[PDB]
Structures are given as C-alpha cells and as structure tokens.
Image: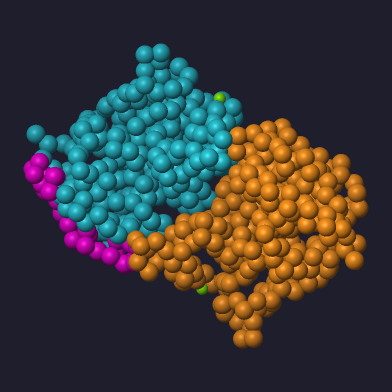
Chain colours: A cyan, B orange
Amino acid sequence: GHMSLFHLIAPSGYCIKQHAALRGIQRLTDAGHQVNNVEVIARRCERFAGTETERLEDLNSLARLTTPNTIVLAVRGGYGASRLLADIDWQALVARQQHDPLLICGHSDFTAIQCGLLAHGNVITFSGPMLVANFGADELNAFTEHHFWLALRNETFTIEWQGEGPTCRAEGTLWGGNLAMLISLIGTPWMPKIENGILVLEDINEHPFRVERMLLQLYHAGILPRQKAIILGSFSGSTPNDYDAGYNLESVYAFLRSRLSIPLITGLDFGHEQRTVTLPLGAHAILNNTREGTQLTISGHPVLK
Amino acid sequence: GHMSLFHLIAPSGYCIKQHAALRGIQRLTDAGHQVNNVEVIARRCERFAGTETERLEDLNSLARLTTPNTIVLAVRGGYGASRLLADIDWQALVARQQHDPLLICGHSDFTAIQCGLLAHGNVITFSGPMLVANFGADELNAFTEHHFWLALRNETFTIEWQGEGPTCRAEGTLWGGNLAMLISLIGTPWMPKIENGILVLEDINEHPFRVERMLLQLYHAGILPRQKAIILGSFSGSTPNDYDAGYNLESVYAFLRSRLSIPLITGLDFGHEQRTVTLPLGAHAILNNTREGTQLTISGHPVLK
Ligand SMILES: [Mg+2]
Ligand SMILES: [Mg+2]
C-alpha cells in the first residue's frame, strides 16, 4: 500500500524521551516502513541533539540523499535550529529539491529551517508530525496519521473543519507554522516575504498576551495585512491565569480582527496537540469558509509516487 | 534637597499589588515628593490598567503637562503598551520634549514606548525604576534609589561595576532595555535604527535558550554587529532546568561572543532585580572596561534643574 522510507534528522533538542522515539521507530517499522539514520536518537550535546557540527550535517547531508520517495522526518523540536541557520548550505539544499525532492516534514523549532527553505528557493516542506511527539505517542492519533498520508500521497487534497470567521473565499501561497519561530526570523535572511498568502499559525505554552504580542508584531511589520487570509491553529497550554481577569484567546482574536481587513479563521487542528493536520508550506491553497464549514484545498506540493 | 513632582502613568497591566503601589506613593510623599495622577492605580480593564482609551490618554496627555521638572513614572509593566503604539501622538510628544522636557522613567513593557520615542524623535527617556516594583517594594533598595537620583540630577554621571569582557573603550548612543520588548518591535515603525551604539539588554523569566534566540535574532537582523558594544544586564529567573544539562547563561554569552567582533560586557545591575541602574536611552555613553573594573559615563540627557 504505502510502505515507505523515513530518514531521521535531529537539528533541535536532545531526545530525553528515549522510550518514545524508539516506540515511534518500532511503530513505523511494524507498519512496514523502514527508518534510516536511527543513530541521531542517541546524540547529545548539553540541551541539543549533538554538536553544532553534527546537527548541521544532518541538514547539509540531505543534498546527497538520493533514494526515491524519501520522507525526511524531524525527531523533535525544542531549541537549536536557530544556531544552524547561518551555516546551512541553502543553495545546495534548494538545488537538491528541484528534482525528485525529499519529502521533509516536522513542526515547532523546525519551522525556522522550513522558513529558510522558502526564503531561498520557494522549497515546499511539510509542517506536520515528528517522530517523538506524534509517531511515538502512547497511541498514534488516527486523525494526525490520516492527514499526514493524505498530504504526502495526494497531489491535490482538502482539509475540512468547523472554522469560525467570516464566510469567504481566498487563494494564495500557504505559509507559516510555529508563531514564536516565525517571529524569531523577522528582519533576518530566512523570513519568507510571501504576499497575498494564506498564513497559518500555531503555538504552544505561550500565554494569550504573548500570542497577541506576536500577532501584533506581524501586524505592525506589515506582514498580516499583505496576506489574503490568516488561519489560526492550535494554541496549546494557553489557558488564563487569575490576573487575566477575562483576558483569553478570544480576546486576542477580537483584538486582531478589529485591525484586519482580511479574514481570520480560527479553530484548525494544527500544531502541537495530538490532532494536527499536515500543511505543505509553500504550496497553493484555496480557503473556502461557508455556513456549512471550512475547507482548505491544497496543491503543488511533492508527493510519494 | 531634591523634593520633586511625580506624575503617574499606567499604559500596561492592571495593578494587582494595590498594597505595594500605595506603599510606593506613601514612601515618595513621606520623603517630600508630591504625586499626581494617583487615580491611575485603581483603573482596571481585564488584565490592563484601564481601557484602550484611558491608557492611551495617559500618554497623549503628556503633551499638555507643563509643570517644571516633572518626573513621569510608569506604575508597572506586564502587557499593554504594544496595543497603544499605533495610536500614540508621537509628533505631539516629540514636540513636547523639545523644550523643558518631562523626565520619563520606567522599564519592562514600557520599553516599547521608549523605543517609539527614540525612533520618531531621538527623545531621551529613562530605563529605570517603576512605582510598584521599585518604590513600592518592602524596602526601597538603596543602590537603585541612588542610581535613579544620580541620573536625574547629574548632566554627566558614571556607573561602575565589575563587568566581564574584554578590556576596551567604546563610545556611542546608549539604547536598549527589555530584550523581549525590543525583539517585539523588529520590522515595525518603533524600532530604533541606532548604529554605532552601546546597546544594553536585560530580561526576566526568559529561559537561557529564549534569551539566545532573541540575541541571535538581533545578530541575524544585523542590529548587534552595527553597534560599538553590547552590554548585558540582569537576566532574572533564568536558572537551568534539568533538561538543560549544562546549558545556561554562560553558554549564551559564549555563543554570541563567538559571532561578534565587538565587545560584549556582562554583569551590569540593570532590569528587574531589586538592584538596577537607571539608563537614559538615547543619551551618549562612554564604555571603559579595564582590569580594575567597568565604567559607563553618560551625558546628554535632561536633568532636574
Ligand atoms: Mg477584521
Ligand atoms: Mg567576539
């Protein structure tokens, strides 16, 4: 059916949840997949998944990786990608992806690498599950599993959900990912300058006020109002404390909405929850929000042949 | 001696520590100071110190505030200044500060307003103590008290400390403040574009990896290497967790140092600890680090006559 090759990379934090990574590896292999580069799991340097040299070579070595239909799977997030950005051989990776592209998938910290690929070569990659959090969870979430294989196997596919926002249609380049990581790139060479897009954002363990602060920066930098639509994903561990006294994500949505002339849709399952979709960053998307529900139709990404 | 007028403003979070604000007011008044605009203490709207309208007018009303030698004192930080930035009458405030300037002092969230004043009119303001955290603490810290009145009363003054870094001399415009707030302005109209400066940074309850992430953005955006020197202040609530496995502020300093050709000095008491200096943002500074210690000589700011 869809037995595949996965190739691990670990540009970010040390894998503390050794149990969960080996559980993810075993689950993939029990399903008939094969996993290369399993040695990245053991690697450690302080809080990083190996030395600057080793994490860097995980990425730069992808230019020589030639097996057909290889899924490159980030192990986990944390911190560490930001240290690598200046030393990544962006041209060589962009060149590699022009023919028989690797199918590169991860989320969180990995956003920054995905962003730099976009900035340098419009190279499409997948914001979606990673080895430890998703494949290595106690149960593999079926929604996430479905949506991963849905994107990677179908040249055109549709996601749907009961989103909140105006009834609207919008079309443009799908981009975004982890909000904090996108913010961390403003002003740098790896910030994608995508206008007229569909920008999708999520985050984890950011209090609402921080989420607002970040969205407002994207607003004030002129990024939000240049898009066709904004979609908000999951904002995990973002419940009010006492001091908030009614201030919550709803307030954040209201505050940004009062400044935007373009639609903002919320409620997509995307980011760090056990339910996440897989979004090909740099692909084409058509957003349609009606009274019956929301759809996002995506095309242009590379798929398993 | 130096009995003065203070005028409160509250652009940020609701004052939950009512006890501490009234304690700060009482301490100032027991010393012979007078405090106006004491009604801002009661104000509340969700997590903010009043409605958008009310917090905004705290700032815009400063243009009509004409008493000689008025110290405008921010009550507290939190979140809220970012919501105001687009609606502040920057020109009117810049114009006000051209003659008989208000002496405006605060830290934390207030950084963003201080930044916008710099960006629009090179208007000097003071990164230093606020009503609740500093004047309203159980004891008024003598180091902080001394350094506050030191800056406000002396046209030229010198701070000294046992800083760590290369032996060096550097000269240029003093700028910076709260690191997270400075980051939140990158790409926006309120980011100061100060080259050849002395950039001083601090923060609170940011883990080291976040501190690094922010410093690296300032590095990758081209801001750090355009300065003459970088000074790091207090980084409060920034001790490692278990996962860090040796990763700490020292690592952060090392990592940035390996990328910078300009000196980076650490160890200044500046920011959120009970000991903080008061730095006039936009003033002229001469940094001198020798084997005996570090000095920073500052001039050009407005003072009490
Ligand atoms: Mg709107
Ligand atoms: Mg250096």
Visible in this render: residue B84? no
In this rendered view, identify the residue nearer to me: A227 or B82.
B82
Rendered view: B267 above or below B178: below
- Residue found at x 72% / y 32%: B53
Q: Give the range drawn in magenta.
A: A26-53
Rendered view: A128 above or below B156: above
Visible in this render: residue A126? yes
Residue B38 locus on image (x, y percent): 79, 44
- Residue found at x 35% / y 66%: B245
- Residue found at x 44% / y 22%: A164
Horizontal side of residue B278 vs A113, given as left or right: right
Q: Is residue A47 magenta?
A: yes
Q: Does the magenta stretch include residue B278?
A: no
Q: Quadrant of residue A103?
A: top left
Horizontal side of residue B26 vs A10, given as left or right: right
Residue B242 locus on image (x, y percent): 35, 62
